[PDB]
Amino acid sequence: VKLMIIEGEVVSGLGEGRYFLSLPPYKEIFKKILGFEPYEGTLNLKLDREFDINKFKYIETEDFEFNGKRFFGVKVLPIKILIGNKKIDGAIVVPKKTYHSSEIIEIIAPMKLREQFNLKDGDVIKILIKG
Ligand SMILES: Nc1ccn([C@@H]2O[C@H](COP(=O)(O)OP(=O)(O)O)[C@@H](O)[C@H]2O)c(=O)n1
Ligand SMILES: [Mg+2]
């Protein structure tokens, strides 16, 4: 086991994180796994290379039905979010089935990080992950 520190650049998406994280079943999944109710959104970070989550120990949930529609399970990887000298509880989240790795990762946390830590696009933060 190694603790890895990785840097990423804050970027904007199309608001997808707030869609999913506001849905009751996803809220419940994250609350149970992580022990906090995430702020409804994902802080999207651009890394210098693709992130392969299958290189880490994560929890994976199954697809589920909500109000007549099938939704995808998720892979959940606990992290610490490193902003200055603060270590903030969070997680990396990826859809259960992805067909390649991405240099963009989605981070969840108990608070809105942009608001609490004044992050803007292009700001670089770090994350700590058990590998
Ligand atoms: N824990 C979080 C989650 C999202 N966010 C931000 O909260 C807003 C809504 O999240 P979102 O995932 O729907 O938006 P995008 O990441 O698609 O821009 C965005 O500005 C995210 O960067 C945050 O500051 N802290
Ligand atoms: Mg997002």
Image: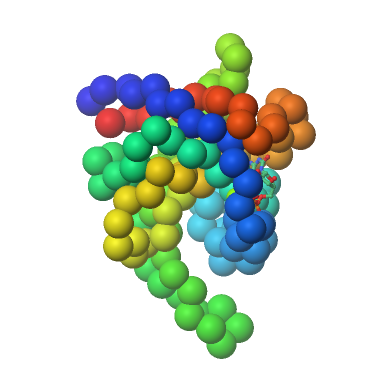
Render colour scheme: rainbow
Nearer-the-camera pick, 109 or 16: 16
Q: In this view, does 58 lie above or below 4?
A: below
The quadrant of the image that shows the N terminus is top left
Residue shown at the point (56%, 25%) measured from the top left? 124
Q: Is residue 64 above or below residue 107?
A: below
Task: Please give left or right for residue 62 compared with residue 26 in the image.
Answer: left
- In this view, the residue farthest toward the bottom is 68
Nearer-the-camera pick, 102 or 2: 102
Task: Please give left or right for residue 115 compared with residue 30 in the image.
Answer: right
- Where is residue 26 shown, x and y percent of the image? 55, 61
- Where is residue 45 shown, x and y percent of the image? 52, 39
Residue shown at the point (35%, 56%) measured from the top left? 60
Q: Is residue 31 above or below residue 8?
A: below
Nearer-the-camera pick, 70 or 11: 11
Quadrant in the rendering for residue 44: top right
Instruction: Tell me if I can see residue 37 in this picture.
Output: no
Residue shown at the point (54%, 32%) measured from the top left? 9
- Where is residue 8 shown, x and y percent of the image? 49, 31
Task: Please give left or right for residue 59 compared with residue 108 in the image.
Answer: left
Instruction: Tell me if I can see residue 4 in this picture.
Output: yes
Q: Say how many tags the image has.
A: 0
Quadrant in the rendering for residue 108: top right
- Where is residue 91 shown, x and y percent of the image? 49, 41
- In this view, the residue farthest toward the top is 85
Residue shown at the point (46%, 44%) measured from the top left? 105
The quadrant of the image that shows the C terminus is top left
